[PDB]
């Protein structure tokens, strides 16, 4: 008597990272997701989400070992847009009717993000990884426009509780893998316009903007036949602009 709502969506976006050598920065990305909003007190609810995203990576070779070559200064040390990523989220929600035309919902919960990227170097094919446990808060408004039409501006903010960057370098004779804590945060903003058509079913669409940042890691070193070497995982800043299309059951 205040229904379960299930939304499946797809986004098409332009995503870019933080490159320091006049490179092409933009990548096409796509994400698919499902959200379940399940009421339990009918002011209060649970929100669950799962998602899967991809961007194409194009093979670009690099001349380095362990992944830091013959001379120290700066040249790898891979970060940027992930090739594949999955996200999961579970949280609680609270919804208030502001007027007969307007609903206000806020929520908070726990999220998990895991992504992978493949790197091909002369000697190796390495895989980088970013795995993050995070806290997320979200807020949105649902305003009725008439005839079943609605607009739904939304926002969310997240911050890492424990986010780690990994690179399977022990495979490229450092004999040791890289696993460094790299906490950050992110935010998202958008607005959907939709049409609630003939009971329980809605179609909606709208633009969105997202930003994700990971802080530079603490210092660490590795073992090279030609030495110890100092490494930092670089501050990483991702920006996404896109179009989301969703179906709400
Ligand atoms: Zn570009
Ligand atoms: Zn999405
Ligand atoms: Zn090697």
Image (cartoon, rainbow, N blue to C red):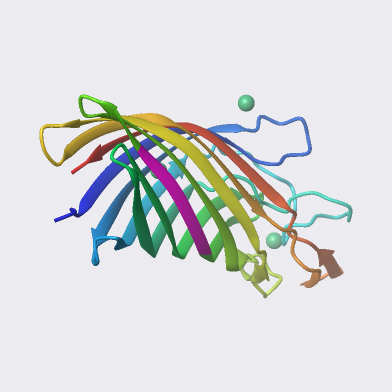
**Of residues 50 and 155, which is closer to you in this image?**
155
Residue 192 image offset from top left, x and y in percent: 38, 33
Where on the picture, by quarter, is residue 7? top left
Say if the magenta span includes residue 104.
no
Residue 90 image offset from top left, x and y in percent: 37, 64
Task: Judge whether 54 appears above or below 91 on screen.
Answer: above
Say whether residue 235 is left or right of residue 106.
right
Q: Main secondary structure of the magenta part?
A: strand
**Of residues 120 and 113, which is closer to you in this image?**
113
**Of residues 22 and 6, which is closer to you in this image?**
6
Per the rendered image, the range of residues in magenta is 135-142
Task: Judge whether 191 appears above or below 2 on screen.
Answer: above
Say if the magenta span includes residue 139.
yes
Q: In the rendered image, is residue 138 in sight?
A: yes
Q: How many marks?
A: 0
Which quadrant holds the C terminus?
Answer: top left
Q: In the rendered image, is residue 224 in sight?
A: no
* Ligand 1's quadrant: top right
Say whether residue 24 is left or right of residue 234.
left
Pick out the residue farthest to the front.
Answer: 99
Residue 136 image offset from top left, x and y in percent: 50, 60
Residue at 20 percent across and 24 percent down: it is 147
Residue 164 image offset from top left, x and y in percent: 61, 67
């Amino acid at each position: 008597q205040t229904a379960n709502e299930f939304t499946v969506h797809t986004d098409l976006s332009s995503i870019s990272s933080t490159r320091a050598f006049l490179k092409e920065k933009h990548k096409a990305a796509k994400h698919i997701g499902v959200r379940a909003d399940i009421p339990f007190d009918a002011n209060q609810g649970i929100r669950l989400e799962a998602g899967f995203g991809r961007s194409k990576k194009n093979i670009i070779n690099l001349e380095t070992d362990e992944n830091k070559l013959g001379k120290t200064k700066n040249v790898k040390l891979p970060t940027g847009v992930p090739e594949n990523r999955i996200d999961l989220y579970t949280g609680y929600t609270y919804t208030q009717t502001l007027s007969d035309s307007l609903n206000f919902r806020v929520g908070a919960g726990l999220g998990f993000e895991s992504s992978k990227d493949s790197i091909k170097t002369t000697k190796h094919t390495l895989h980088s990884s970013r795995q993050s446990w995070l806290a997320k808060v979200h807020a949105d408004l649902l305003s009725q426009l008439g005839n079943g039409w609605y607009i739904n501006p939304w926002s969310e903010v997240k911050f890492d509780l424990n986010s780690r960057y990994k690179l399977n370098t022990g495979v490229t004779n450092l004999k040791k893998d890289i696993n460094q804590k790299t906490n950050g945060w992110g935010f998202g903003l958008g607005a959907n316009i939709g049409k609630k058509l003939g009971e329980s079913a809605s179609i909606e669409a709208g633009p969105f903007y997202k930003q994700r940042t990971y802080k530079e890691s603490g210092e660490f070193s590795v073992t090279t036949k030609s030495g110890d070497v100092s490494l930092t995982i670089p501050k990483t800043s991702i920006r996404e602009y896109g179009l989301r299309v969703g179906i709400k059951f």
